[PDB]
Amino acid sequence: QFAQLPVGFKNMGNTCYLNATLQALYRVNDLRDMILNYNPSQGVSNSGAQDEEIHKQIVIEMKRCFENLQNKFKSVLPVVLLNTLRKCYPQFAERDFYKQQDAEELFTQLFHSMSIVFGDKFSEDFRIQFKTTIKDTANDNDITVKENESDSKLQCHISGTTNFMRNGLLEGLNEKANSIYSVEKKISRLPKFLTVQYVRFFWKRSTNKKSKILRKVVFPFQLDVADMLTPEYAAEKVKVRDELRKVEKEKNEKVMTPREQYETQVALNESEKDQWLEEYKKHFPPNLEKGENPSCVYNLIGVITHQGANSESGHYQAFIRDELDENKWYKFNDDKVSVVEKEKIESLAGGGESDSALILMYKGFGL
């Protein structure tokens, strides 16, 4: 009666890559907020970027789109945003409709633009820092440790052996006169928002053509990455996790018109949610960096899926967890929005030609 369905973006013809990506970004609370409050008078953070003005326009056009989503405009047509994106990143103007594109490539370029415009305020929420150990496979006294590698996502490598996301994340942290060196990353700083890429798209050698790995790879709703951290950082994050678990457990224990009553209940539920956020926050570590995850645990909040033979075919969708009711998920099939249950989300692990998870977004536990 009173609860309104979220709205989606109309597909202009092979532009579901953009639509699914925008829903996932909109779900990231801090990002949504900084875009919604962006004032062009504020300029950009990185005015070393030669194309500064077009990045600012990308943000402006995102803000307009986000204003239309927030204020539910039954359908949003991101025409000007697409044109703007194409001016900045001509790869997205390739034809053959315009050609279908890899959502990962869009995600990456949008991250670049948002980093130019907002700076550290944006990028610190996503930064993963590594401690890298570099050993000569032929000599285990030749050891070098580096602390300066970082990224804004983790890659989940998928081969025929891969059955769970953890398997692929662990493989992604390792790689290999001249010698073969093993290069082994452990995480020394976790972000509050953790993006995971399933490496599904690849160049098939046999056919000289783009293809896709269809293998089922199970992801968890609650992700714990303690085993990917340096020993020193794990000790810190596990201590936090164990206090947060105690709060979670304690939480699980505990004349107006009909419209007015609904609006009062929403207000009550938001207050109760905020009181629990404050209870978790009491246990956050004292020297936590802005944008850093307090613990080593995350909850899943969004999934970008793809169905089709390769990154230039088929269809992308987003599945987004409701911000209050953690059991509720929304399916954004462009402008067709529906409510689905946890079982439908689990089925996105893949296997065969089914719609399957490509990019996963996790938010830190207790946030």
Image (tube, grey):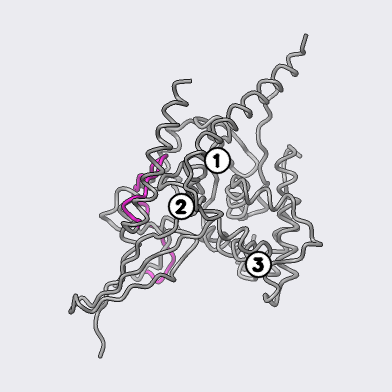
Circle nearer the N terminus (2, 1): 1
Residue closest to the eye, 343 or 221: 221
User: Where residue 173 appears, x then y in whole percent?
Assistant: 34, 63
Callout 2 secondary element? strand
User: Where residue 97 appears, x then y in whole percent?
Assistant: 64, 60
Extreme right residue here? 41
Residue 228 within the segment the image draws in magenta: yes
Q: Nearer the viewer, mark 1 or mark 3?
A: 3
Looking at numbered disc 2 in the image, what kind of residue is underneath it?
A: Leu
Label 2: few (<14), some (14–19) or many (≥20) C-alpha neighbours in 10 Å: many
Extreme front residue here? 286
Circle nearer the N terminus (1, 3): 3
Callout 3 secondary element? helix
Quarter location, residue 246 = top left
- In this figure, which residue is indicated by the disc labeled 3? 116
Quarter location, residue 54 = bottom right
Label 3: few (<14), some (14–19) or many (≥20) C-alpha neighbours in 10 Å: many
Label 1: few (<14), some (14–19) or many (≥20) C-alpha neighbours in 10 Å: many
User: Where residue 24 appears, x then y in whole percent?
Assistant: 57, 48
Instruction: Classify 39 as above or below 250.
Output: below
What span is colored magenta in the figure? 207-229
Instruction: Classify 139 as above or below 267.
Output: below
Q: Nearer the viewer, mark 2 or mark 3?
A: 3
Label placed on residue 320: 1
- In this figure, which residue is indicated by the disc labeled 2? 358
Q: CA distance from mark 2 to mark 3?
A: 26 Å
Looking at numbered disc 3 in the image, what kind of residue is underneath it?
A: Ile
User: Where residue 140 appears, x then y in whole percent?
Assistant: 19, 75
Quarter location, residue 297 = top left
Q: Is residue 323 left or right of residue 129?
A: right
